Image (cartoon, rainbow, N blue to C red):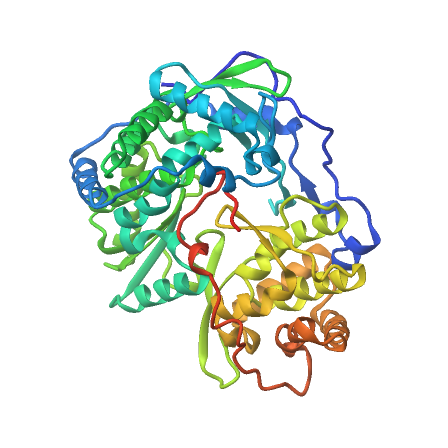
Length: 560
């Protein structure tokens, strides 16, 4: 049972690829040490291929089947509808990868006659053929990072043609948005805004007599997912009340695509064969979450960890429980790891028990504290700012499809670093370019959105509350981490940012309107004599419903 089989053909690039950060006046005003930032390229693919190609020995036991039982029962609750081809098309991102069969994402969102007739045909074929492998393309993924303390290989993206992706949406969008919540309840991480997630963690932590927690990183999770795993997911999906055609398409998608298939490079050559999770299908986030939850829940029972609560987001897992002592927590964690390893979810970083909630990193994030205007304590979500700042420098130098910095400002608005640096840097640019009013693409939980910078104040208030503009007195841990990171990257110190912010604020106020409102609210931290901020009228009435329903990483999803 090998995760991958290779022919010798290479993972080829489609364009030329940049590795180094472009020395640029703007970039440099944010980040001086440009030689610490790199982007992944095809050149490192051979290395990723070695990490990722192995034989999986999986062995299931009583605990695993008792848990599956509970999950299938909860899935039986669910009713899911077939998306009409119209709806599926409008879910396609405008810059999605074009079809091999003579049309692109625009034609799809336009319901162009050629696109829709092809999609219809792909569907017909799905209904009638449940065994012929569906072709997937494989690419080296391009992401920027900062150089390691103690260098990362490109990740491998694997995805089917555009026509197939629209068919996935028709068959599975509703399922994939609705099921995980029903199946995992409050453990489903993607139903929560960053604030809600924090409330969950802190409340869970406080309900324990003596709390112990840990995160669990499994090594190359997609690599470890077996064909049996994928079949189990399918059976969970089939617990829904589904339209007969939906059943047929889902079965066909699982058998022809999800469990495996042939790998084709950009130059049309066969690279090999996959018998594990594809990173770029609609089900990869839902599927990872379910599978991770299923293995982790059973391992928790094997380990006899007591009063376990867990939170799961794709391959990311954190559990909080009652401590039974130092030496026995330690031993239980080894028992849990041995169970995951048998279930074919071996560890990357060996896991260690933590007794301070602030020290537990999950989704690269962690909970912290500050104080609002009234001195009241406020918990909020933060993370190490290294990657976000690296990517911010890159996006300052090279325009880009996805604007990570915008996603980061939204998700991490209350943070010390996103306020003083990210907000300040990017508003001064927009200001000078004069593109305040222009909408930009970012992503949130994998899904893509188009967002107007001048709407940031309403958005932030709605997601984080008014205190997000008044936080101060951050934790020692946060302050030190951030401080140490600016020194690391050659980022100008926070007193400089405060100075640039005063000026950006003044210019925004200058222009009145929504822009002055950005000035008032986003930059009040910057002035000595602070303003009383009162609730925004346009916030109390925002459609933020569909923002935190599910995860869609690699799912190719776009919202209005």
